[PDB]
Image (cartoon, rainbow, N blue to C red):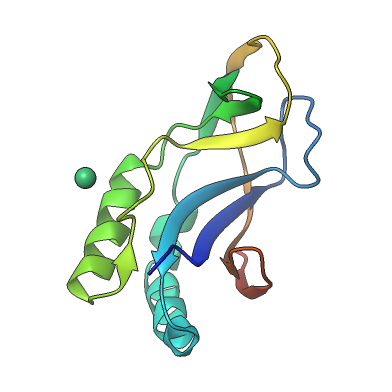
Length: 141
Ligand SMILES: [K+]
């Protein structure tokens, strides 16, 4: 019953240098059977307006753990609560193991904090992907 799917968000802009291929926010983590993907997609579609209304911002980078350098993310709390609650009610396992500490990993290196003026991260797309697997759904505004 290990986490096996993520809901990710990719962005039009990232105001920091980074070494990862494509920076993303892991917004949510799921444990599901593959045949539940349509149901998860249905919920993502129902919540599409709400998700794309999020005002995601960033203002500094930091070390989250040894060798994990990340950008902070703000603006996703209330929407996280809503989607958490919808999945919970629907008996779809979501956010049962993942700490809520929104961040975007930038590099696997020990690096100093950079601070910028608060910057909005424009959402490029929101997707559902198998952990260490393929993206099975992607939506744009
Ligand atoms: K807990």
